Amino acid sequence: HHHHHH
Amino acid sequence: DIVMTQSPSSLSVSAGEKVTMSCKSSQSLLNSGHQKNYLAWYQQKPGQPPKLLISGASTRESGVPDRFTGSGSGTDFTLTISSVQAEDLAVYYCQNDHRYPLTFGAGTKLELKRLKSWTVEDLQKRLLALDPMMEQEIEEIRQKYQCKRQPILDAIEA
Amino acid sequence: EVQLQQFGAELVKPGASVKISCKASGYTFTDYNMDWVKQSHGKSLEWIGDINPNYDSTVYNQKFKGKATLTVDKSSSTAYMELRSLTSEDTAIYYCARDGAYAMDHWGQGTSVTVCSGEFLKSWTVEDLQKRLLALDPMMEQEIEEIRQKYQSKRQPILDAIEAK
Image 1 (cartoon, rainbow over the protein chains, first blue to last red):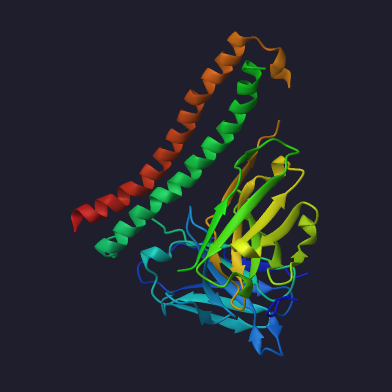
Image 2: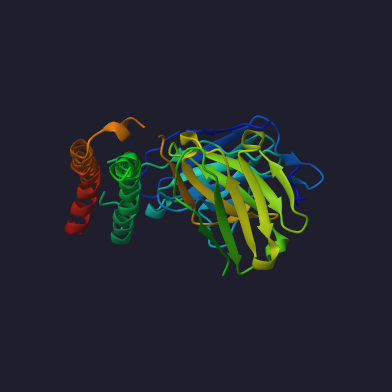
């Protein structure tokens, strides 16, 4: 979904 | 759920003074697989959106002077201005850029206190900075009073 | 150069729904998420959520679940936020920001959403309505002139310093 947001 | 705290809230300054804002997160911002602390700093002047100064705790964006240095790790971070200039008189925010939900600090405002120590260009920039500052407060008055007029207007024509 | 241009209605009645628009130019729209940020008058910043344009996947701050809906139109490089069941508490400037690997490195200019808080005036006469309506601008002027005097107090010491050099 995102590069590193989780 | 991560909570950001900055200090101090406000900060008087002067020509060429070094300033240091703290940012402390309730949980580590350290992504160990990425080998990266995912903390970001923004500079916001009145009337304008926030502007990214630093990402990943220490990485200055393009057009950000070397005077701005981010440092820290885990849950403790600082943003340092080696030689303060007039254009740096803003509000500064740190941001959890690490885990959902993304969260923001409340801010640290560089309010100048009280002048000949400044250059001519620094006093000009600070003067030109007060106009969008004033416009923010004034524009807010107009907002409040624009609402009070609406039901009155609708009621006249029913 | 990168640009995110914001459009949308400014003034809404309570219970309205408003669809804010964010038009991205100067970069591959699908290569970045899009964040939405609320800034209330207290200057408090609150992240509402993001959308991935490639998958239409969303993530919401629980606080804004239902209150906000995030859509994209990949064809036109446009992201949308729909604010629903508007309350006076929803009055704020709303930003879209681009979010890839380096946090929110470009921001729209912001769309100011003002929700008037909103009956008794219906029964008032025309004379009394115009009276109240006439009293508000003198009031609004005096309140602004306080601000102009507040900032005149800060401009004067800087002007003096320039005049001496």
